Amino acid sequence: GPLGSTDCSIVSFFARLGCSSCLDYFTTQGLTTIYQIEHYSMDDLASLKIPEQFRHAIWKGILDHRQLHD
Image 1 (cartoon, rainbow, N blue to C red):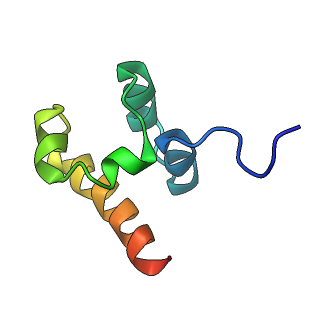
Image 2: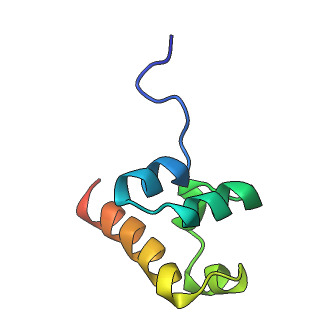
């Protein structure tokens, strides 16, 4: 049986936030990870063909999470 965790990627993070199509794109590209977005600043995301309309939101959500928690 699992032990709390089972799969840890941006998929679960998008599910909570309400992000739908953006999660699809991420899992389809095969580059969805939590610890990576925590190091991949706004520039890498822009170079990943991610538009500002969503890019700054993804980054803001995770940076806000790690900022509000420990």
